[PDB]
Amino acid sequence: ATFEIVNRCSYTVWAAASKGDAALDAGGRQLNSGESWTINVEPGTNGGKIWARTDCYFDDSGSGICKTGDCGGLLRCKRFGRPPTTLAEFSLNQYGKDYIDISNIKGFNVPMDFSPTTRGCRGVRCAADIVGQCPAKLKAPGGGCNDACTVFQTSEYCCTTGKCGPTEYSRFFKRLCPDAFSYVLDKPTTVTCPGSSNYRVTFCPTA
Image (tube, rainbow, N blue to C red; front, side, top):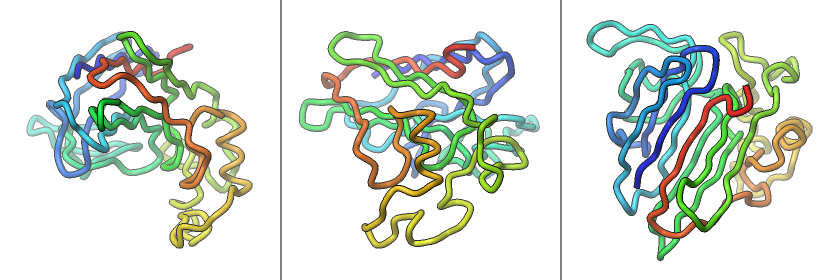
């Protein structure tokens, strides 16, 4: 599958793509405002994620730090990033179908649209000003709005027992972005697409 990753933000982001134990394609790249990066994701990829990182500094060797979404200090991510990270999530060619969603379960840093570029399904978007409206106790100093599990580490927020309900914090994310996951047992907002669809992920789709 092809993913086009587009930075429509007025600021530079460092895109990342990983399935948790490996990079997808190159794994990461700098995107200046307006730049597009096309990657190729192997069919059958389960549990892939794409996200943006902000305020990064990398040396020549591709080693450094980012204020949101850092993946162990690497430009080319092999593992998932540090919250807060708005997440584009996908599993491809699962019994004939692709499954895509946006998630705020690991917080929010950059607004996002995640849409197919081929026919047969709809896209999803979370583009509200979640950082500006973020509850005081969830604000991340480096930027972004943390999820409550990251901040408080309780069974209820992290849904550790497999039983949990919505919370005042999850409802905040859900109010602002109804089409994104707001906690682990949220009513699924997953979209089913034809297997082997292609996609575009746009950072800052409205601005």
